[PDB]
Length: 304
Length: 9
Picture 1 (cartoon, each protein chain N blue to C red):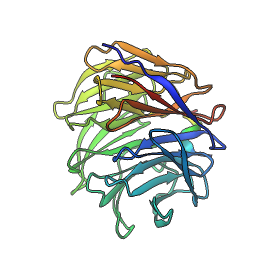
Picture 2 (tube, rainbow over the protein chains, first blue to last red):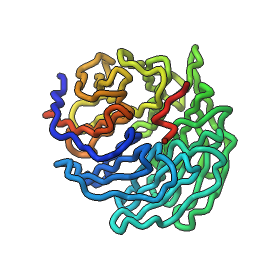
Picture 3 (cartoon, rainbow over the protein chains, first blue to last red):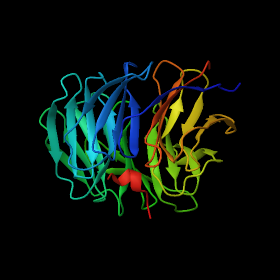
């Protein structure tokens, strides 16, 4: 079985490279962040522009939804994160304390904490209600490319250009595990699987890898795309068939069968690197977004 | 700009 993703909508309006797109957990919305210092909200099903959220002083590398779809957090070159009330557009809090660009961010499943990673080589844990930094982890020896909470928030996974993925205990801040394979390329992305058993890690040697982090074993590798320079998001697609979805530096979206590791689809149409992809939580919908020479977001839909 | 959009050089 193979999906049949087809282009449905192209979303224009960011004035520089897009950096990340994320569907709201309730499926209603797509949020996008850009080097143009803006967040934009779009209808998830029709791509209709909803609103622009502004206030960062420099470009934004990442944005993420709270689990109730009410809040966003963004990570900016202005070395802050910002917590936004999406409905009002208000900036509820500005999270300050990284000493270099903030690159990646996520809420925990409760959405009472935020985790961030930065060019300052640190991972930080922040209280959502007060905006105060609770912990600073001396996590890596190079910029932190991704941070993600596991299913119950007990764990944080981080990835870094230093070649490592690390698993941290949220409560204590202890480093519980370091994961690295036989080669040491920079790690450009990591996230836990939906069931929390696995981590999916991207490295800048054109490779995605599915790990059992408890056993510290690499279970699957996904290849065929181009990824040597950019921190490209990757996703688990679970609404229809079980796929792996990723952008690529050859301007395509790649879709692999999770179990067999075969490429099952490539989506063509962006005019620059596909920096980011997201999978809708209930419908077979992929959002993709591209860099400076393209500046657009595309929505693709499939029957499986 | 934004660091993600620049890549690692």
